[PDB]
């Protein structure tokens, strides 16, 4: 997109400004060096000239740094905007999908299903209670309670516990 | 489904926000470093500039973190919804079978 | 170009929607919670759990 | 991150509740199926013994 | 605040 091309352009510009500042700095160092080497020999005017050069380079480095920083702020705002746009896209997609889902499914279906589940489980509980009652009524002779109590007492004494 | 595509999109967005925050953090660290290196030589304006840059990066990292968190909440709600839908399907099947 | 394509009213509409849909979803989830808790009541007394 | 952790905890709790409810339902279903098998076997026994 | 902090870290005053 134009956004991406412009981001590349801004990154290139920032890198170029940084490199220009670096060059200005190296040049300032070299000029200061030459100033030393010249003054060590008794040169005033050369010193003045190189000093003016260094001042110019410093001012220009500062200006490049300011401009680079401003450009960086702008690029950052742009990235923020692009990210927000991606987010808006994703969110609109989610809106479409969720609206579709809510159109398909509703709450009355849920309530009906749950009321059913309740009734079916109630009927099942009734059936299980009936089965329990019947199967317990069938099995009554071949398990007296006295024998069970005696066995329980015996096995509890064997294990070493009381009931 | 649209749900799955959107979930992928949201995960991508969250990861992208996290990476952007990481980049902003690394850049803040680098700017603070350069501030030190410049002040060690007697530079005020460079220090101010880099400090402004770091503040911007911090603010932007914070904003990305907020947005990412909100998106994460939304995605979580969506996953909840999808799971509930699966559940409703299974339950309707059970209803049919038990009836 | 971007501002011409996208505007703020679309954002506000989307967010109002999101709010309403999430509210409806919260209601549905509350209904599901209530129903599924009403169903499961016998096979978890409170004394046994305590 | 704390907000994130709270969200994750709440969601974990909700998933645990839902999973437990689903487990209860599945258990009831298994009970029903076993009872059906039993009823089948018993009907066969009825036929044979009659 | 940041300038004061970094100047204290480096060990200079502004």
Image (tube, coloured by chain):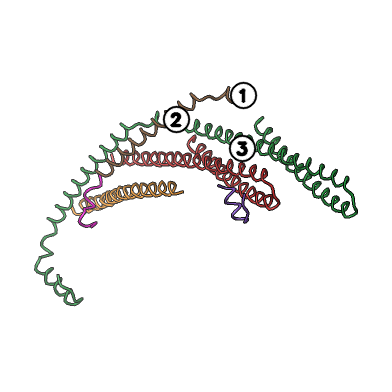
Chain colours: A green, B red, C brown, D orange, E purple
Determine the residue positioned at 63% across, 43% down: B48
Indicate whether residue A135 is drawn in magenta: no
| Magenta-tinted stretch | C39-50
Looking at this view, name the residue that lies furthest to the top: C4
Alpha-carbon span between mark 3 and mark 2: 25 Å
Q: Which mark is residue C15?
A: 2
Q: Residue at x 49, y 33 (%)?
A: A91
| CA separation in Å, label 2 and label 1 | 23 Å
Label 2 secondary element = helix
User: Residue sitting at 69 percent across and 33 percent down?
Assistant: A5
Task: Kindly identify which numbered label has been placed on residue C1.
Answer: 1
Q: Quadrant of the C terminus of chain C?
A: bottom left
Q: Chain of mark 3?
A: A
Q: Chain of mark 2?
A: C
Residue A54 is drawn in which quadrant?
top right
For mark 1, give the secondary structure. loop
Whether labels 2 and 1 belong to a single chain: the reply is yes
| Pointer 3 residue | A76
């Amino acid at each position: 997109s134009n956004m991406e091309k412009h981001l590349f352009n801004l990154k290139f510009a920032a890198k170029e400004l940084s490199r220009s500042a670096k060059k200005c700095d190296k040049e300032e160092k070299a000029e200061k060096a030459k100033i030393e080497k010249a003054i060590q020999k008794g040169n005033m005017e050369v010193a003045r000239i190189h000093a003016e050069n260094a001042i110019r380079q410093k001012n220009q480095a500062v200006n490049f740094l300011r401009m680079s920083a401003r450009v960086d702020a702008v690029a950052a705002r742009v990235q923020t905007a692009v990210t927000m746009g991606k987010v808006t896209k994703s969110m609109a997609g989610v809106v479409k999908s969720m609206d579709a889902t809510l159109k398909t499914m509703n709450l009355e279906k849920i309530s009906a299903l749950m009321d059913k589940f309740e009734h079916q489980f109630e009927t099942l509980d009734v059936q299980t209670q009936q089965m329990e009652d019947t199967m317990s009524s069938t099995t009554t002779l071949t398990t007296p309670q006295n024998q069970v109590d005696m066995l329980l007492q015996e096995m509890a004494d064997e294990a070493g516990l009381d009931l």
